[PDB]
Length: 153
Ligand code: HEM
Ligand SMILES: [O-][O-]
Image 1 (cartoon, helix red, strand yellow):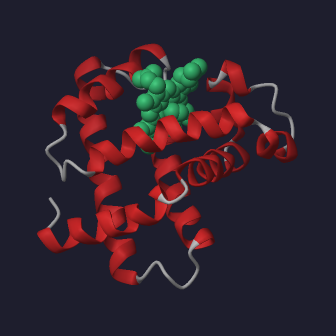
Image 2 (tube, rainbow, N blue to C red):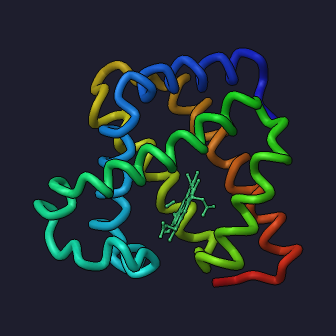
């Protein structure tokens, strides 16, 4: 798991996200969709977004970014004790949304990118290490639930 110090770094970084959750969420999703267009196809309600300008102008995309990062933030604040919060998300993403674990890797990478992009010089090496560990733990616990379900994608 993560040490006390590492969790503290994670939650300090998260304070930066919370100052503009919609903006961070929007940029995370745009990074995901532009870097990996196959991910956009999982969202019937975002398929019409043909260009990045359209993505940037989508108020619904910002709304969804808020929903995603709010869920993630609640999970991070549990500092690993997140079974009850994580289980339903793992199950909805496997059974309903059909999201391969690879796409969770993609979005994890997008979060790290957006943190540097929005806070250049203010996302230190220790903070990146801690946030990476937290996102890996999240992904790994989802992966365990995916294996239970026999879900691949
Ligand atoms: C940080 C990781 C993620 C978190 C915390 C997250 C969270 C959520 C939440 C809270 C919802 C609404 C409730 C639900 O359906 O369970 C949702 C819906 C959804 N998620 Fe995710 N999600 C994540 C990653 C992804 C990724 C990587 C994809 C696809 C590439 C994805 C695809 C979807 C889709 C298609 C919906 C339904 C959207 C709609 O039509 O309203 N999710 N997600
Ligand atoms: O996308 O959640």
